[PDB]
Image: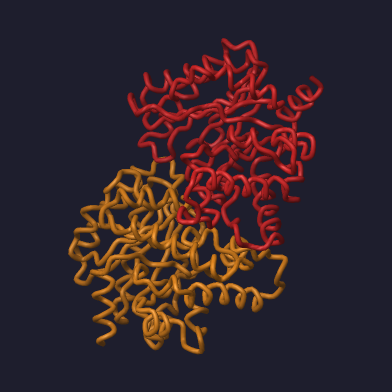
Chain colours: A red, B orange
């Protein structure tokens, strides 16, 4: 209620960025390996999930996460059901760190068709949304993928994204729509042209604001009209394959767009480095992403 | 003589890739910070250069560098004048690690004009080349930058690259030409189209082979005709802003092109991590880049 309204204010006004911690089981080995934990070091799914939970706990409890430069955090569903320092993760994010909690609500992608990969339908979405409200989660995130400058395909991406969004809104949660255009798209600017056009037409019909998570565009500042649309709460940006230094550099050139990075935020961090170095490097990466986010 | 010929064979035939360690003074703070050494930790240029020399020593002496997956290494001039385990760096690379040593021979870039940044002229190049021969260095590397699909500009890039190359050859050194097309180029495929066309026309007039270091192309396999040209020894590829995972993924799709990575090879590594983790992560990153390089 008063959280909600204070969280809404943060998400709309506050300078800073969102950390994406929302890797599904299928994406956790890759994140663990990059943290220096090789697949060879665990051999059950439970052990794997503990291991990534220790990582995220180590991030969230670190002094670097107490800065206010990170305004939101996106969670995997298992993490929301877990604890940090004996306290439900979302609650710890907000009560002890002043970070607005979100949850990834998608169940993965369909096979590519029409140059795009739509989200797998998820019948029990509304059940996840009510569960999230029970954890005081403020918003959601959902990812869909554009591989080509296909008008039908991109039309569909956006329409599925907004359907899911109107449904999520109903539950009193703010959805982040994530229609990622692959950075290796043969015609990226063209695809982003279609995407923008579909996006605005949907926003014109909306009666409540949403957020958007997009690849940093080929044309600097291309998303201005989106950022400025009164039904757009905030625009955040995926790295999508760029290094932290590259994403930041391009991000600096997109006025009003803030970061939403996963593995890029965290490059350099490892299991068996001292706590001192972990916090220092984490603090620096955050400062870098912040300075880029605020331009 | 018999090194030379064994090194030539490695560079032409051997599967694997080249590690680029050739950061100038101007680029060393960025590499140090990414290794967890903040600018704030040293305050002279000598201390900075020691610090990056310890890093490179720690890489080169590590068991991960004894794999044969790395076939060449590119050195900054100061490193060539330094030692590893009391032995000149280039000599240690070859005698103790079976890695072919190269040296970066450029002095930086000119201001952008015609959508490109040519290399600053370097009158004493030939003096550096003779010095390098004295250290038993096998080859050189030189970097020039293409920001736009400008025909005059790209014509010039290539012509300067080959002039420098014919000069370097004279000294009995194999040059790696590096005409980098920025990954954020508004018209990358088009620029790579011009680049390829200029490159082939120069190669048709060559009487001795060279090597090429390029951005991974927008069109998969675009450089085939180059790789196949009898005056092309080997094609290597810069990351140029892609994460290690992204560069590897795209690299896998370019048949016969091997990696030549600097900061991407080394993402995850830090000063204050245990020797054990440093070697493990280094070994894994190398294995990854290798598997991508050999496709």
The image position of residue B159, as x and y in percent, is 32, 62
What residue is rendered at 39% in x and 58% in y? B289
Instruction: Give left or right: position of B203 versus A293.
Output: left
Determine the residue located farthest toward the right in the rendered image.
A2
Q: Using the rendered view, name the quadrant where residue A9 is placed.
A: top right
Instruction: Give left or right: position of B193 versus B64.
Output: left
* Residue nearer the viewer, A162 or A217: A162
Placement of the N terminus of chain B among the 4 image quadrants: bottom left
Q: Using the rendered view, name the quadrant where residue B190 is placed.
A: top left
The image position of residue B74, as x and y in percent, is 42, 71
Looking at the image, residue B145 lies above or below residue A111: below
* Residue nearer the viewer, A168 or B195: A168
Q: Is residue A229 visible?
A: no
Instruction: Give left or right: position of A139 versus B237.
Output: right
What residue is rendered at 52% in x and 77% in y? B57
Please give the count of numbered marks on the rendered protein.
0
The image position of residue B290, as x and y in percent, is 35, 61
The image position of residue A237, as x and y in percent, is 57, 36
Looking at the image, residue A174 lies above or below residue A66: above
Instruction: Give left or right: position of A126 versus B62.
Output: right
Q: Is residue B84 visible?
A: yes
* Residue nearer the viewer, A97 or A234: A97
Placement of the C terminus of chain B among the 4 image quadrants: bottom left
* Residue nearer the viewer, A265 or A184: A265
Looking at the image, residue B84 lies above or below residue A110: below
What residue is rendered at 56% in x and 51% in y? A245
């Amino acid at each position: 209620n008063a959280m909600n309204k204070e969280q809404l204010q943060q998400m709309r006004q506050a300078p800073g960025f969102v950390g994406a911690l929302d890797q599904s089981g299928g994406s956790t080995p890759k994140a663990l390996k990059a943290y220096g934990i090789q697949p060879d070091a665990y051999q059950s799914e439970e052990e794997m999930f503990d291991l990534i939970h220790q990582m995220r706990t180590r991030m969230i409890t670190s002094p670097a996460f107490a800065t206010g430069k990170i305004i939101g955090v996106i969670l995997f569903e298992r993490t929301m059901r877990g604890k940090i320092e004996g306290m439900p993760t979302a609650d710890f994010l907000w009560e002890k760190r002043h970070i607005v909690p979100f949850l990834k609500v998608d169940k993965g992608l369909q096979d590519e068709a029409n140059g795009v990969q739509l989200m797998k339908p998820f019948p029990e979405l509304g059940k996840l949304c009510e569960e999230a409200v029970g954890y005081h989660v403020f918003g959601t995130k959902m990812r869909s993928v554009i591989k080509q400058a296909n008008e039908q395909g991109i039309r569909d991406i956006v329409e599925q994204q907004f359907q899911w969004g109107k449904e999520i809104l109903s539950h009193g949660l703010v959805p982040i729509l994530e229609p990622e255009v692959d950075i290796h798209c043969p015609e990226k600017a063209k695809a982003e042209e279609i995407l923008k056009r579909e996006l605005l037409a949907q926003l014109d019909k909306m009666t409540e604001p949403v957020m958007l998570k997009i690849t940093i565009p080929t044309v600097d500042n291309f998303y201005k009209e989106i950022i400025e649309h009164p039904m757009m709460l905030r625009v955040v940006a995926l790295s999508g394959g760029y290094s932290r230094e590259q994403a930041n550099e391009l991000l600096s050139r997109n006025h009003g767009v803030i970061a939403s990075f996963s593995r890029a935020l965290v490059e350099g961090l490892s299991a068996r480095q001292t706590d001192a170095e972990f916090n220092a490097m984490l603090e620096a990466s955050i400062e870098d992403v912040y300075q880029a986010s605020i331009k």
